[PDB]
Length: 16
Image (tube, rainbow, N blue to C red; front, side, top):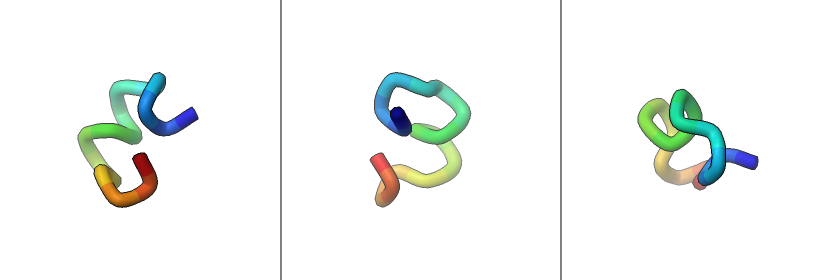
């Protein structure tokens, strides 16, 4: 998921 996936956390903190 976003919060367990470094690129997502950094690009889209909202999605996290």
